[PDB]
Length: 41
Image (cartoon, rainbow, N blue to C red; front, top):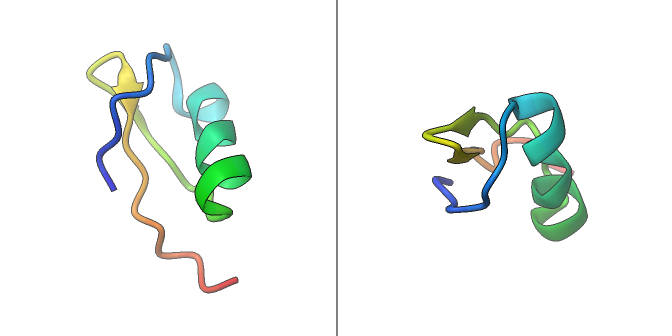
């Protein structure tokens, strides 16, 4: 994962999770990012 990245939708806020944690698959919940870092990579 739950991050506090300010976004509006998963397919937009999950870019920082890819670029940062390199996992993506994030969810823009609570006007914020919410990924799980479950992508092996």
